[PDB]
Structures are given as C-alpha cells and as structure tokens.
Amino acid sequence: KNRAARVRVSKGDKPVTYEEAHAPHYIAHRKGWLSLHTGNLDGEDHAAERTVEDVFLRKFMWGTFPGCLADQLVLKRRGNQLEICAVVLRQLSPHKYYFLVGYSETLLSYFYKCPVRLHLQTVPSKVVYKYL
Amino acid sequence: PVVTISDEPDILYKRLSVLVKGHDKAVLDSYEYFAVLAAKELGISIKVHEPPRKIERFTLLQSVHIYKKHRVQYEMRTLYRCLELEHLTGSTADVYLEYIQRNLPEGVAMEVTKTQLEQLPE
Amino acid sequence: EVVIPKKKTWDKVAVLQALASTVNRDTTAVPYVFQDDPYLMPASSLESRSFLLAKKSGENVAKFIINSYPKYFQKDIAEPHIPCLMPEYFEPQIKDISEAALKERIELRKVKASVDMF
Amino acid sequence: SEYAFRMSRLSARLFGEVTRPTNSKSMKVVKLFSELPLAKKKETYDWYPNHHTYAELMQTLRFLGLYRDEHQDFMDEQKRLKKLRG
Amino acid sequence: AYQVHGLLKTGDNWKFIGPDQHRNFYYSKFFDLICLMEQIDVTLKWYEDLIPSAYFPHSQTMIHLLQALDVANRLEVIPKIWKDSK
Amino acid sequence: ALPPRTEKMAVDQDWPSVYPVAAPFKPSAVPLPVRMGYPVKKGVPMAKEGNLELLKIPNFLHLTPVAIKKHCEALKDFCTEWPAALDSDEKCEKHFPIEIDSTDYVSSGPSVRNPRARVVVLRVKLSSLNLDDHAKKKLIKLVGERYCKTTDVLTIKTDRCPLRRQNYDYAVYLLTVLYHESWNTEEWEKSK
Amino acid sequence: SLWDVEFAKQLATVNEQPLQNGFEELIQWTKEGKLWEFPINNEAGFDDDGSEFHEHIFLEKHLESFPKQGPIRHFMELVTCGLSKNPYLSVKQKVEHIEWFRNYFNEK
Amino acid sequence: HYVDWRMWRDVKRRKMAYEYADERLRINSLRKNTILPKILQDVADEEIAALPRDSCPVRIRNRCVMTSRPRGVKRRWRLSRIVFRHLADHGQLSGIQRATW
Ligand SMILES: [Mg+2]
C-alpha cells in the first residue's frame, strides 16, 4: 500500500489539517507547494542549496518556535527577500512572539545574507479539516 | 520627484521581449493582464505570445530495497508566456522593467528579458 | 531627422519614493512596524513601547551572539559584499606593543586596554 | 585546397583560435585550457554543505537555550537512563 | 494648531515629529484641542483619521472625548467610542 | 484577541494605502471571506482566517487596476518619447543599421551570477553597410559558417570574455576588423 | 575626525524615525545594501580591474616571444588560445598560468 | 558532525582536490599535447604519478547531500531517491507533481 504522506484512519477521533490530510497525488491538484523557490524550473543552477536551506529553515523555525507552530510554514522566496509566513498559535505571550521574530529575522538574514522577513499569523487552536 | 536629465542620447531599445517562465498558468496570465494594462496606460506597445510548455518527467524507485517493477514518476510543468515589447525607450524600458521586477512573482516566476539596443556602426 | 532624447538618470530610491507618495498613510491601519494579527496588536502606547523594546532587545540578542561567534557566519553567499552583514570584530587582533595596535584599540573603543598598553 | 586552407588560417588568426594546422590531439589541450577542470567547478567544491557551521551553531544555540531540538532531548534522556542502569 | 499641522504635512516634518513619546504627546494634546473647540463631525473625522493609525490615546483624552460629545449632545456615539476604548 | 479591521473597514477606502507591498495573505487585513480547499462531502470550502493555501497563493492582492493607474501616475515622470523612426522595419534599419543581442537572466535567491547572461551576438545587414563588392566576396569567404543566403544578415557570436560590455566591444571590434581585412586587398586573390 | 563622525552619527540618531511602511523598509534596505541593485545586469560589481577586452584574449604582451618557430612557442599559441577562450578565469590567473609555464620551461 | 566517515572522507576529497587542481591541469595538458619529446613527457609522468592519489577527479563520488548514499542520487538537487521522494511527497518542493500522462 501507498503511505508516502497519507495519514491513516485511526478510529474517527484524530484532528488533522488539510495538508496532512491530503495525499501526495493531490500535490498540485488540490494542495499546492509549501515552499515557493525558483530553483526547480527548466533553467536554473542553485536549486540544490535552495533545498538544503529549505530543510534547514523548517527545522530551525520548528526548534526556535517550540510547540506553537500550528502546521508547516510557507517558505516563499522572491528576488532576495525570503518570506517565512507562519500560522503560529495564541498560547505564548506577544513579548515572546516579537522577541523570537526579531531573533529569527536577524539570524536568518545573517545566515543566508539577504532580507529575511517573518510574517506571523496568530490562530487560537490548531485547525481541524476533518476527523479521521 | 528628482529627475536629473543628464547628457547623452538614448540607447534606443527595440524589442525588449520578456519570457516569463512559471510553474503556474494562473500566475502567468494574471501577470500578463498586469503587464498588458501597465503597458497600455504607459503608451508602449505590448504583444502576447504563448511558447509551448515543457514537461520534465523522470522516474524513481518506490521501495527502498527491492521492487524495481513498481516505480514512481515525477514531473515538472515549465510553462512559458512571452510579452514582447516593441518601440519602447531606454528610460521607459528600465522604469517599466524596474516596476515589473519589483512586482515580479515568487519562485513561480522568471523574467528572461531580451534587449535589442540599435545604435550606429563604427 | 531623429529627435533622439538624452537619457535622464536616477538613483535606486526615487521610484520607491514616488511609490510611497502614491501610498500615502492609511488612516485606519496601525504602523507597519507592528504585525497585522489582531492578537499581536498593541492596544496602548505602553504595550506598543513594550513590543518595540522587545524587538530591539531581540535585535541586539542576535548582534551579541553573532559577534560572540563570528566563525559560523564567515561564508558570504550574497554578491556584492555586504560589510554591514559581515561580523564586527571587537577583540584586538594586534598583540605586540605597537602604534598600529594603539590605533586598533582606539578604533575598538577599549579605554582600559588602550591606557594599559599606552 | 591551398587557398581554402589559408583562408581557414586567416580566419583563425582573425578570430583567435590556433593559426597553424594542428590536430585534434592538441586542439584538445586548447579546449582543456578553454574550459575549467573537473575539480574547480562551483558545484564540485560546494556540493556538500560544510555541516560544521550548521551543527555546531545548532549545538551552541541549543545550549544557550535559544534552540530546542527533540532528537538531542531524546539522546540526553536515554543516555541518562543508560548511565543509570548500565 | 491647524497651521502647525499643515506645516507638519508639508514634506518630511512627519519625520521631524521624532520619537514615540513626543508623538503621543503631540497627537494627544492636538486631539484634546480638537475636542475642546471643534464641531462634533470634524472631531469624529479626526478621531477616525488619527486613532489608532497615528497614536494610542490616553484616559484624559477619553474623558475629554466624553466632555466634547456631551457638549455636542451626540450621545448616540457613546457605545462606539466605548467599544473603541475597551 | 480583537475584532479586526476587516469589519472595521468601510467602503470607499484607499486600497493602495491598505496594501503597499507584496505581502502574504493576512486574513485579518483581507476584507474578503475567501474560501479555499476541496470541500468535505457534506460541507463547504474551508474558511478564510487560517488557510495555508490562501497563504501559499502568490497573492496578487497588492496590485489592482486603479492602484496601477495611480502607481504609474507617479511613474509617468520617468520616460521620454520616441522620434519619428517609424514602425517601418526598413526605415529603422536605414536609420540605425546594426542590431545586438545583450541580455540578462533574472534569478531569485542569494546571488545573481548567471554566467551565460554575458552572451552577446551582433547582426548587421550588408545592404545597410552599402560598401562591399569584392569586399563582400572576401567577407563571405571569411565568414562562411554564418550568412544564411535567404536573408542578408551577418551574425557574429561572443561568449569568450566574462563581462557584457567587453563582449559588446568584441562584437564591434570583430565587425570593424573584419571590415578592414575585407577591404585590405591581399596579393594572392587573383590565383583563386 | 571623531567629532565629525560623532556629529554624523548623532545627526543620524536624531533623524532616525520608525519605518511605518514596507516601501520604506525597501528604502532602508537599498540604503544599507541588503536589497539587490535594480534593474540588475547579472554583473553587479565584478569590475575585474578594468580589463577591457584586450588583456583577456590578446596575450602577446605577457607571451614575451621566444623563437617563434619552436614547439615551445607552438605550445604558447595553444595555451594562449585556451586562455583567450576562458571566460571564467581573468587576466591575473591567465598570466600566472603563463608564468608557471615560463618558470617550468626555464627549470627544464 | 558529518553524517558519516564516508561523507567526511568525500569532503576531504572535494576540498583538497579543489586546492590541488591547477598543477594537475598544467601537467595533464603536458600529457595530451603531441608536440613535446617523449622523455620530456616522462618526467611529467613522474610528477603526476607523485602527485597525491586523493585530488584526482576519479575518486569524486556524487553522494547525497543530506544523507550519504552513493548510488541512487539525482544531481539537480544532490538528493537520494527516497529522500527526494519524501520531500517532494510532503510537498515542500515546488513544481514537482506526480507524472500522469
Ligand atoms: Mg502500488
């Protein structure tokens, strides 16, 4: 059986989002892409390090925003502005939120050497698309 | 509004053609409508063209150890849309290019611009 | 006869200045320094000041850890080179008793070190 | 003929390739000095990330407490129990 | 006050406003003056134009809002400015 | 949380003022209950306030026609106009003979180094050069591999030097020295 | 000296204002150098000391002619054409290659 | 702090081959030009045969950029088969769809 990115039906009590719910064969038919970088088209050179920085970014934001990221980020990349757009929860205090935003802003601008912008979006609870 | 008309005559760009490559036809034709309306109110001449899409298809194994007979196949859709500009100035050219490259889309956009400055022989 | 016009020249700034003059201030929106989430809105001036000082706190957070560990970041990827993204070195690299080291720690603003080696 | 050979020579001198008639076995040396070798290519010497800046920066940030990685949390707890009993 | 505000809107005198505390004092006393001797329609227009886009008003400014609305006898606006204060 | 500017916001409000920059979705700022998603069987498309698909859409909510109209009201300063060089291709060929390819390849990331972007290639017309008879014979005999017969276009390629301006210099230098060596009569032309 | 740079930095601090717009964020990023220079030529910086097209491909001046009938001079013609057709290397590494061959040939 | 000793051995190969590329380039041009005398090429044969056997681009194995796997690597992202499948199936990789033609 295929279980690349398909969450299995447990008993009918399992909160799941659109992205975890949808299967990899709906990747451009229903889902879309979580990272928008230009490396993967016909003519381009640096897509490999685009990908390695992509996975670096995902693991780093998850490690530095502990237990508050609802689902996976949107890692947009245009020109030299990186965009980390987030779906962060409403548990920790906004002073902590702004502190970590500035911390991440500056370090990622500094590590990848460009304008790096984090745009948070606050959500009360982790959203459920269906119960499986 | 600093302007500074300085010294030397125009670089005389004829046919600045913009090939916009994308993963997404909706991004490509929304950007087409954007560029066409911007060029229309600029007064420069715009023409539309659709170069055919290229699909980069390739094959990988599905299991980690055995089972070559069951393979997965991945694809890339690289769609091209051409916005050729004829009869546009050098100053109009780099201001229009500056605008459309500020509002260039993300990873679903590349803007390959072909500039034909004319000049005199020497 | 060709009336070929001379090319008027600008900087990198005037186009975006005219764009801001197009976007005059939004009478209903908060200042852009804060975010756009209703939970992240400052409600009072004290809350806005606390948010801003927390943000400047995080700015010098990264500045401190970066200047403490410049080795992890010496790899530049951006071209052209950005010296204000290059590390600032605060330690004196010149160790012998010399006037070059004197100018060095004078530039590094180390008062006691400059006095002691003078 | 001879005229075509010396027109090829004249075009070679005009454009910048080798003037005198030379075989492929040294025309290849000209291509070797016209391209880069296998080791000097940017993808060849930047194929790997250095991993040391990455891993040691995450190490430093975690033990500064600015980074929380559950894999290292797992190894800390498991080695705590393993030194407790082993 | 209007002539100084016009001088402010000329050019980069909005940059010459300066820090946040000076800006808060600026717009607070300006809007106190507006509520003190302007008519209620343009006080409400300045209210929606300045608050909260320019600044965060104070409690003294709140009680002056109430005094201005009581003078104008426009007590139908009380719930809206109340929800804004909350 | 707070009641948002979506319903605080009222009609006839300036939208270039609302969204200056290309920004991600921000549903509280968006005054539009936009719904994404493949719906569930007995349900509707998923709502606005938290959609990562709304977020992943490239978001051309910073550009509408009246905004672009006002943007280029500002941007209309930065242009001259053309002379009467005419839409006629033969007329502009008569006025300005040579034609040159000199491009850029816009990437997106840390660095803007696309080396192939220094490609430069020159096309010129013999009928606009107007000064070649046994010189044009000598010209063709020099550049055999170019000069397709059906159109009188000469195309000389340069991708040998790293910078675009010196590639243009190689193009014009090759043109003038091919011209001068064509007009330089050689002593063995007669024994053809 | 430090009084005029101190006056400059204190003037900067007293004319430092909140960003208040994303276009002004782009303005400050252009001023610092974070944002790319636009319209971009794929050759921002990278002057290569004003080489200007003859030092890259015409290497007679660094060729320093030997008896030109020799196979050593033929090798010089071959390597000169190769270094002319290099676009990734510049004149400085071209002439240090040339000098490396000169040194080795003089050693032998 | 590398993935394994094989990956660290490979990055040793890359770094010091990139250092010792130029001399090898000069002397293998001196191999495969047919102008010089044979003994004058034999001394050059001695110098490259003495040049170390870790900088020659014959030991360069294009392993996967995340996790060391020699065979089964796509060059365009330096990724292995199943790691590329994992990532382009979770959907963090733009433009890769499932090929259904
Ligand atoms: Mg199957």
Image: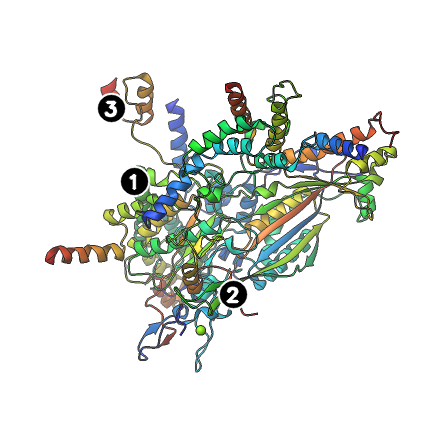
Apparent side of residue H59 relative to residue A93 in the rendered image (left or right) = right
Of all chains, the one bearing label 2 is F
User: Residue F130 location, x and y as percent?
Assistant: 86, 36
Of all chains, the one bearing label 3 is C
* Circle 3 Cα neighbour tier, 10 Å, few/some/many (<14 / 14–19 / ≥20): some
Under mark 1, the amino acid is: Phe
Under mark 2, the amino acid is: Val
Mark 1 and mark 3 in contact (Cβ < 8 Å)?
no
In the depicted structure, whether residue H45 falls above or below residue G69: below
Label 1: which residue? C64
Secondary structure of the residue carrying numbered label 3: helix
User: Residue E3 location, x and y as percent?
Assistant: 48, 44
Apparent side of residue C23 relative to residue D74 in the rendered image (left or right) = right
Q: What separation in Å lies between label 3 and label 1 (alpha carbons)?
A: 21 Å
Apparent side of residue B70 relative to residue G69 in the rendered image (left or right) = left
Secondary structure of the residue carrying numbered label 1: helix
* Circle 2 Cα neighbour tier, 10 Å, few/some/many (<14 / 14–19 / ≥20): few
Query: Nearer the observer, disc 2 or disc 3?
Result: 3
Residue F11 - label: 2
Label 3: which residue? C113
